[PDB]
Amino acid sequence: GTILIDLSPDDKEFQSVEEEMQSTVREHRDGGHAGGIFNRYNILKIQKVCNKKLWERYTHRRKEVSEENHNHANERMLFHGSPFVNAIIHKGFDERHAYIGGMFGAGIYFAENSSKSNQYVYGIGGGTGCPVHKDRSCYICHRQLLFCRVTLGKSFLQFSAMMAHSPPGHHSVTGRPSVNGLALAEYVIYRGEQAYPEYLITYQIMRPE
Ligand SMILES: O=c1[nH]nc(Cl)c2ccccc12
Ligand SMILES: [Zn+2]
Image (cartoon, rainbow, N blue to C red; front, side, top):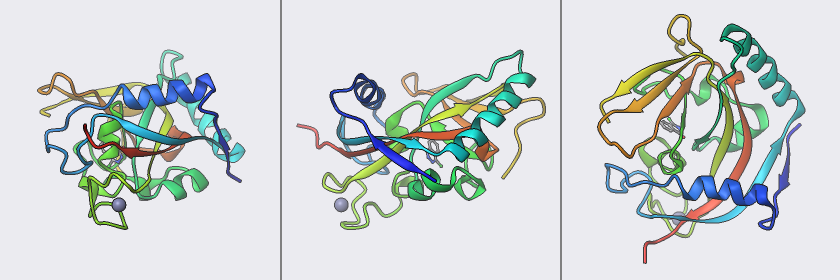
């Protein structure tokens, strides 16, 4: 079902996706423990993920949510890092991609900061790092992130001091850091059909000069 189309680095689509990656790196409170130490990426490949059944499943949900929310899907593009990226692009998001222990209950988490999603590429809190070197700051091994279409609908705003259900009458949760003024929002959805893994980004973190 799924096919991957490579974007040309010469294509403005590839460049705006790269731009969204690079411009949303920030420093993290763990000093790089989970995702490694870096200020920018070496982007290796960007692919468009194409799956007609998964897309129809997404837009069918999007229209439902839209209809329930002052005609507004509230659709965003957000990063998602996960060791199960191969399964997500083939079979879609589901409960086995839910972060049981997350701050906003058991759902599927996305971030505005690419560097926040990079923390999850090798597992929760970076797991034990790359499979080859066991290094959470590995500069050699190739990482992948998804840059996804996410339907938020009516989003419950939850300020944070940094499968379950949406709070009644809402279709997601906005987790908004209230202490770190440079940290962008995270978002949690509770139905796999509310996200589509539109781009697959293959990259390395770069060692700071
Ligand atoms: O990109 C992400 N992937 N996985 C998780 Cl649990 C997560 C949790 C918070 C913020 C971002 C992410
Ligand atoms: Zn490695």
